Amino acid sequence: GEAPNQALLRILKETEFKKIKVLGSGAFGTVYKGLWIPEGEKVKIPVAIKELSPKANKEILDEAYVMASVDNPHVCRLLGICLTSTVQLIMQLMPFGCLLDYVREHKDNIGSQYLLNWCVQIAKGMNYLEDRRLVHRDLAARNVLVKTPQHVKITDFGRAKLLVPIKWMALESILHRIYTHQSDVWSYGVTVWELMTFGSKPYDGIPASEISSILEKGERLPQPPICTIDVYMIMVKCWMIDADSRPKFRELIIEFSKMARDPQRYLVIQGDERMHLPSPTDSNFYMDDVVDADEYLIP
Ligand SMILES: CO[C@H]1CCN(c2nccc(Nc3cc4c(cn3)nc([C@@H](C)O)n4[C@@H](C)C(F)(F)F)n2)C[C@H]1F
């Protein structure tokens, strides 16, 4: 019926990696910036290490299962796990952090080209997850990470399933707990709104229990000031009541790619194209034998 999942789960020794500093901390545990120095390979790989009760152990292994099973340039994969007293997930270091914080902090240097290219990349990553029959269930700008300003990836498979974030959820999901690739499209629309408003909070000040009612009446997130009607119409289509009436991720790739070819026709930003963001062709952008996880293949 379903294809065998032949993904390899790499078990890493504690001695092969070192923690440098804390990147983030929450109820889940803590995420560290680190370096992975495998076997006798002559490589140093920058990594994010998530360090974690037997039920929270099952939750991290379920996320590890999904994360080890993906392989796409716009999705974050699991590099390996370490089985210590506490289970650790070894992931790629995304040095610019999450896209949500990035748009808030670099707003004055974010042009239309970057915003539209990020929409294309997220749609590509989501289309890949759809090809793998994976429903994300938690797509949001907080769960899109920045490898470089020109390269983003979807992460956080903590809610991902085969075949709660109320303000990012489709109406069928809030009311009936129905999740499909089309409910991920709704979240995609909310994520694009977060990018276009440079990280505004959706339905700010409105309690989560009031969202279902507000959506049923037909209220939607407002048109961001930089968006032309062309961009907003796309967002609005992601928020149709009929799931099948919403665009598909494959069509979202096409639509945002056409717009990314003439970005100033679709997003109106003051001082656009005179804006500068770090690129791997900059002084001290990037230390001996350091290799990015994307260039380090198999054991
Ligand atoms: C709740 O766990 C999440 C944590 C983020 N995850 C993730 N997936 C793949 C790569 C990756 N690397 C990654 C994550 C990073 C990072 C650099 N690289 N810098 C930050 C801070 C400064 O913003 N973070 C956040 C999201 C946090 F600290 F929370 F992790 N991080 C996916 C899940 F493990």
Image (cartoon, rainbow, N blue to C red):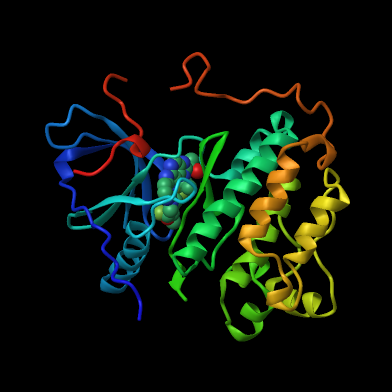
Q: Nearer the viewer, residue 231 or 37?
A: 231
Query: Which quarter of the figure is the C terminus placed in?
Result: top left
Residue visible at 32% across and 61% down in the picture: 64
Residue 174, how many percent across, how many down?
Answer: 64, 79
Residue found at the far top of this picture:
283
In this view, the residue farthest toward the bottom is 176
- Residue 198 shows in this picture: no
Q: Is residue 116 above or below residue 52?
A: above
Q: Position of residue 155 (x, y in %)?
A: 47, 54
Drawn side of residue 288 relative to residue 126, left or right: left
Q: Foreground: 265 or 45?
A: 265
* Residue drawn at point x = 28 percent, y = 19 percent: 288
Residue 95 appears in the figure: yes
Q: Nearer the viewer, residue 98 or 188?
A: 188
Q: Is residue 243 left or right of residue 65?
A: right
Q: Residue at 51% across / 65% down in the picture?
A: 130
Q: Is residue 40 left or right of residue 224?
A: left
Q: Give the quarter of the figure containing the N terminus.
A: bottom left
Question: Where is residue 296 shown, x and y percent of the image?
Answer: 29, 37
Count of numbered marks: 0
x then y, percent, for residue 238: 72, 65
Image quadrant assignment for residue 39: top left
The correct choice, above or below, for 85 with respect to 184 in the image is: above
